Image (tube, rainbow, N blue to C red):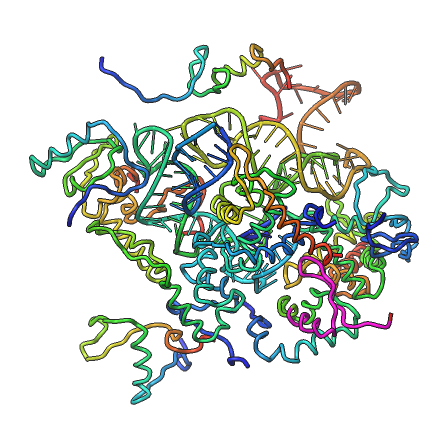
RNA sequence: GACGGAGCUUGGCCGAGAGGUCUUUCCGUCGUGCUGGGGAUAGAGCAUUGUAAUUAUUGCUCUUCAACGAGGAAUUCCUAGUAAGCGCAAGUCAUCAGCUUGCGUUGAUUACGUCCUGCCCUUUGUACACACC
């Protein structure tokens, strides 16, 4: 009911910044992942914890 | 004072002293049997090396033997162990101890320490007392 | 005419007709209480 | 020809774990002192069924004996005397070590402070339930003292990352120095607050 | 001298416990008891006392390989064909995801079996017939 | 939960508590107020782990700055210093 | 594909009678057919009879027994015999 | 406290547990963690009892890791080897949760008094009398 507040948070990465995240990001999630995840658009998205990726959990 | 000390020290200071002497024997083959879970629920072997599983089981059994005798595979197994009736939610412990005992007893036969009866059980030999008593010699001097 | 079997198991008196019972002596578990007064066996006269 | 136990090659030999003396210990409170026997103990143990007998001076007591027994017990469940003696053997040594004074004397000091002047039994009479304040009866002061000191030590062990012996020493010293941090003194001061007021 | 130390593990997938010593820490790995755990340490050649977190990178990498399948021990599925489903795969260790995701299949397989164990999976009820005098009040 | 630190062994290994800070501050500073204090009381007051205090005592022991006695439950007393006798 | 004598189980193997055993090769030769009304739990399952119509009568109802690919390394009475889950 | 090791029945080769026979209380570990707590439930598979173990055996390798943070309104006993706690064997019994039941082992606190409940004798009243239901 407030609409002014922070409900969520987001990052737009483009360019090399995008590629480095794609490299780690693709590697978790195994593969050959499914075509259904892909959109009509030529887009895909998957979900998973931030904890996945080379990262300190601490 | 020393020989009689085989019999007459508190068991632990006896076992602790004795285990270093045992360490010298060539034998001490565990071959992978121990690895499953020898006893109740948290029994594995890596703390075993200093005076573990295996090595105290020998060292002491020998401490026990001097005083007592005759013995056998059975006698040894629960000496140590439990296996109490259960109010049926439990375990306390499962001590197996059928595998354990067998491993300790086997090594001893090779060196020549323990002998096997027809009815009687495990008897100590001339060889068996000699090593125990001779090491006891060192023990008493340290203590006092 | 042919034959049959199965529902073997333990023993009980004649004096009482129920299956369930205690074996050593050979009668049922109340027949055993009747018997307990008697003495017959070395022991039980009575009382505790 | 000897060999044998090492103690002193003798004298009168103080026992009480072989470490400490009992005779030196003073009970300041003249009333209290009478009930608290320390004319000739050790620490071994003993039962004896002295029987409840009332009004005059009731029975023999050792202060120490009462303290070990409460610990095994309270609480709750599943405590053995070999461990129970052990924890005290150590506790006495921790207490001595903190105070630089005889552990029995500190125990006394704790108990004398924690034992309230007055109490508050709950009596129904007529249409309602009153508390008029009630007698202390000299053993009951002692019993309550030990129990309170004993619950406090337990409560601490349970909650915090501490073995009993230290919690028991801490609770006892703290009572023995009149600090409200101890459970035992805090309850003494409460019980005497309530009893004086409810009259 | 340090490491700037702390630790985050993926381990099997997405899981961290830590701050305890390796043998005890390892039990928490899906797949190992106290009973499995100690053996894996000595086979890897890490000490018992050392924490699963505290280790250096090379020692931790050996843990990842060893636990999933080790040198002297191994288990390959063998038998003649079929039976098809379910099979045993010679006692999967292989524990962790592959165990948890295995039973999910094993359940449908047990249904295509027509087992009671499979019909109960379909009925939805307490599997191996629990007492009803009292119980199950937290559960649902 | 609440949370959570001193926490050992990883803090034990790294310099931060082993080097000087813990042995000199915690163990050595306490001793001038009480000649001896028990290993377990000393654990609790300092807020230092039992295992953590135990290696530190052992280094110190070697040094001859402190002297322990014993008891089974790895309880005992810890004393620093002492004397002419 | 291929079958061999021998099959593993748990402590279930030995002698026996004849009465359900004898009936079971009959649907093989005659061809697939009616269900076979056997209460008899006693029979350990064997590969030869696979994919054939069976029955068991526990007591009051019949319960269709069909042998599946999956119902192989099982015990036979398990399905409809265990539950009597005839309640909802 | 929890862990491991240590303080009809065999001998002994031999076994994951369960078994088959040629054969008569110290110290590693714990970090006070809904966990190394707890074992609930689930699932596959192995031996024995029996003809059979699936609704209705027991033991489980192995792996799921369930509630429950010491328990409301409330209760029961117990007067020192008794409360309370550890186990064992007998009977049960083809099998079987522990029933019921005895032996030892561990080992405490309170015990004045009648100051809700059962009772005793006397006492009075009684319109009750299968009896204050």
Residue E11 is situated, as x and y percent measured from the top left of the image, at 40, 69
The image position of residue D85, as x and y in percent, is 73, 51
Say which of F56 and A53 sits in front.
F56
The picture places residue A9, in percent across and down from the top left corner, at 39, 81
Q: Is residue H23 left or right of residue F48?
A: left
* Magenta stretch: includes residue F51: no
Residue G38 visible:
yes
- For the point 68% across and 76% down, the residue is F23
From where the camera sits, is residue D141 visible? no
Q: Residue furthest left?
A: G30
The image quarter in which residue D112 lies: bottom right
- Where, by quadrant of the figure, is residue F32 drawn? bottom right
- Residue pushed farthest front? B126
Instruction: Find the magenta span and give its range.
Output: F55-84
Position of G78 with respect to E135 (left or right) is left
Query: Split into 4 quadrants, where in the image is the C terminus of chain F?
Result: bottom right
The quadrant of the image that shows the N terminus of chain F is: bottom right
Q: Is residue C34 above or below residue H111?
A: above
Q: Nearer the viewer, residue H71 or D104?
A: D104
Q: With respect to residue A45, does H115 lie above or below?
A: above
Count of all numbered marks drawn on residues in the image? 0
Residue in the picture at 59% in, 80% down? F15
Whether residue F10 sits left or right of residue H112 in the image: it is: left
Q: Position of residue E133 (x, y in %)?
A: 44, 39
């Amino acid at each position: 009911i407030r609409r002014n507040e922070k409900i969520a948070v987001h990052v737009t990465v483009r360019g090399p910044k995008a590629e480095e995240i794609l490299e780690r990001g693709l590697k978790v999630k195994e593969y050959q992942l499914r075509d259904r995840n892909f959109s009509a658009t030529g887009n895909f998205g998957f979900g998973i914890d931030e904890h996945i990726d080379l990262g300190i959990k601490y | 004072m020393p020989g009689v000390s085989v019999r007459d020290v508190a068991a632990q200071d006896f076992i602790n002293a004795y285990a270093s002497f045992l360490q010298r024997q060539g034998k001490l083959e565990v071959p992978g049997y121990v690895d499953i879970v020898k006893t109740s629920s948290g029994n594995e072997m890596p703390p075993q090396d200093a005076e573990g599983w295996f090595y105290k089981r020998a060292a002491s059994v020998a401490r026990h033997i001097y005083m007592r005798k005759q013995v056998g595979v059975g006698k040894l197994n629960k000496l140590y162990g439990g296996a109490k009736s259960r109010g049926v939610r439990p375990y306390k412990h499962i001590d197996a101890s059928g595998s354990i005992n067998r491993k300790v007893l086997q090594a001893l036969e090779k060196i020549g320490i323990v002998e096997i009866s027809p009815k009687g059980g495990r008897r100590i030999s001339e060889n068996g007392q000699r090593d125990l008593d001779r090491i006891a010699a060192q023990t008493l001097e340290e203590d006092e | 005419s042919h034959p049959r079997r199965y529902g073997k198991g333990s023993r009980q008196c004649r004096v009482c007709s129920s299956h369930t019972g205690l074996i050593r002596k050979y009668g049922l578990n109340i027949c055993r209480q009747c018997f307990r007064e008697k003495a017959n066996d070395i022991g039980f006269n009575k009382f505790r | 020809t000897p060999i044998p136990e090492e103690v002193q090659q003798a004298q009168t030999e103080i026992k009480l774990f072989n470490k400490w003396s009992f005779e030196e210990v003073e009970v300041k409170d003249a009333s209290l002192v009478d009930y608290v026997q320390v004319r000739q103990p050790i620490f071994v143990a003993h039962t004896a069924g002295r029987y409840a007998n009332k009004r005059f001076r009731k029975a023999q007591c050792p202060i120490i004996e009462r303290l070990t027994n409460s610990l095994m017990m309270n609480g709750r469940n599943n405590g053995k005397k070999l461990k129970a003696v052990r924890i005290i053997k150590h506790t006495l040594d921790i207490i001595n070590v903190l105070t630089d004074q005889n552990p029995i004397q500190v125990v006394v000091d704790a108990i004398t402070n924690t034992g309230p002047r007055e109490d508050t039994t709950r009596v129904g009479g007529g249409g309602a339930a009153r508390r008029q304040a009630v007698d202390v009866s000299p053993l009951r002061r002692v019993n309550q003292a030990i129990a309170l000191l004993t619950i406090g030590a337990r409560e601490a062990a349970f909650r915090n990352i501490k073995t009993i012996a230290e919690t028991l020493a801490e609770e006892l010293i703290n009572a023995a120095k009149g600090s409200s941090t101890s459970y035992a003194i805090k309850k003494k001061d409460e019980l005497e607050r309530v009893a004086k007021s409810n009259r | 001298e340090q490491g700037s130390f702390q630790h985050i593990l993926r381990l099997l997938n997405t899981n961290v416990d830590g701050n305890i010593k390796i043998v005890y820490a390892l039990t928490t790995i899906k797949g190992v008891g106290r009973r499995y755990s100690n053996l894996v340490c000595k086979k890897a050649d890490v000490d018992l006392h050392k924490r699963a977190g505290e280790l250096t990178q090379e020692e931790l990498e050996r843990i990842v390989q060893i636990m999933q399948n080790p040198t002297h021990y191994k288990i390959p599925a063998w038998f003649l064909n079929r039976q098809n489903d379910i099979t045993d795969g010679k006692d999967y260790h292989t524990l962790a995801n592959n165990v948890e995701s295995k039973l999910r299949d094993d359940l449908e397989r047990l249904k295509k079996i027509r087992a009671h164990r499979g019909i109960r999976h379909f009925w939805g009820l307490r599997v191996r017939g629990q007492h009803t005098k009292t119980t199950g009040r937290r559960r649902a | 939960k609440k949370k959570w630190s001193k926490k050992s062994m990883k803090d034990r290994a790294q310099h931060a508590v082993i080097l000087d800070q813990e042995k000199y501050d915690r163990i050595l500073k306490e001793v001038p107020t009480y000649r001896y204090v028990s290993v377990s009381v000393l654990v609790d007051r300092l807020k230092i782990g039992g295992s953590l205090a135990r290696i530190a005592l052992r280094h110190l022991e070697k040094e001859g700055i402190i002297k322990p006695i014993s008891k089974h439950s790895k309880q005992a007393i810890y004393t620093r210093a002492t004397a002419s006798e | 594909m291929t079958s061999k004598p021998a099959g593993f189980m748990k402590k279930l193997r030995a002698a026996k009678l004849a009465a359900p055993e004898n009936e079971k090769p009959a649907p093989v030769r005659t061809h697939m057919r009616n269900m076979i009304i056997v209460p008899e739990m006693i029979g350990s399952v064997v590969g030869i009879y696979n994919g054939k119509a069976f029955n068991q009568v526990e007591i009051r109802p019949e319960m269709l027994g069909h042998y599946l690919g999956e119902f192989s390394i099982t015990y036979t009475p398990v399905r409809h015999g265990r539950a009597g889950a005839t309640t909802s």
